[PDB]
Length: 306
Ligand code: HEM
Ligand SMILES: [Ca+2]
Ligand SMILES: [Ca+2]
Image (cartoon, rainbow, N blue to C red; front, side, top):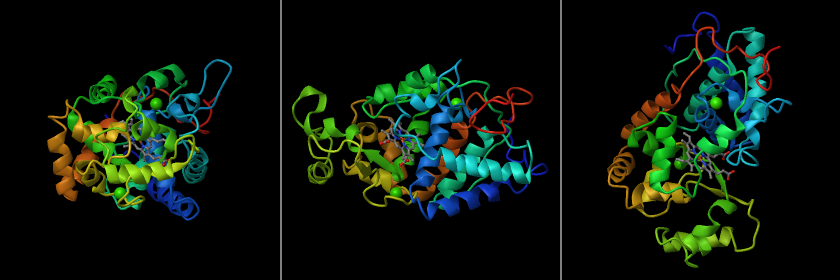
C-alpha cells in the first residue's frame, strides 16, 4: 500500500528539494510546472506510474518518448534529471524516479496556485519502457467523449469525476496549433469549424493558427489564466471556449449527461474542483504501481540500473 509518509525517515527533505528545483526552473521557463504535471499523467497511463516514460532508447526496447502523444510534445526531462541528482546527493539510492515524478507533479500544481497535499509514496521504477502501450493508451485531442471515457477506464479510472477533474490539468500549459486545425477550418470533413467552439474565440484562434501556417505554434489552453492552476478551465467550457475537442466535449458531447454537472460544479466552486482534483490525482497515482521489492530505485532516471 502506498503511503504519504514513505520518505519521512529516509529522506524528509525530498519534497523541498523538488520544490526548489521547480521554483528555480520557473524563472527561465514559466511552462515547466505544466510540463511536469503532464509527464506524470503520461507516466501513469502507461503501465502505471513507474517512471517508464523517463527511460531512453536501448537496443532491446524503444523509448515512450517517441510515442505519438509524447514526440515533439512531452518536455522537462532534464529538469527531472536535475532534481533526481539533487535528491540522490541528499539521500543516496532512496527515492524512486516514479515517486520523484509524482512529487514533482504535485509541487508543480501547488506552485502554480493549485491545492497542496501530500501524495502517497512507495512506488518503484520499471525495468523497461512501453512504446506500443503508450501509443495505445494515451488519449488524443480528437477523441470523442466515449473514447475519452474508454481511455480512462482502460487504465483503471472508471469515474467521470476522474476524467472531468483531471482534464482540469488544462487550466495552464500550451497546445500546438496542429491539434485544433480541424476545429478551426474543417471539422469532421464538414469543411466548417467545430460548431461547439465559440465563434468569437474561433476568430482569435484562427488568427493564432492560420490555415497553412506554423502548426508547431503554441497557444494557451486557458485563455483566462494561462499559467495559473485554477478552476477557470471549466468556466471556459461553459462558454464553449475549451481549446481542444476533448476539452469541449466534457460539456457539449451528446454523451455528456454525466460530465456536464461535474463541469458546472467545478466551475462554480474552486474548493469543489480542488478537492476533486486531489482525489482524482491520487487515484491516477495509484495505477498499477510496483511496490516493495518489485522494480528498482533507479539511480539515473534515463536508464535501468545495471
Ligand atoms: C483527457 C484527455 C487528454 C487529452 C486528449 C490531452 C491532450 C493534450 C494535448 C493535445 C496537449 C498539447 C501537447 C502539445 O501541443 O505539445 C496537452 C498538454 C497538456 N496536458 Fe493534456 N490531455 C488530456 C489529459 C490531461 C491530464 C489528465 C493532465 C494532467 C492531470 C493533462 C495535462 C496537460 C498539461 C499541463 C499540458 C501542457 C503541457 C506543456 O505545456 O508542456 N492533460 N494535453
Ligand atoms: Ca509508466
Ligand atoms: Ca488557469
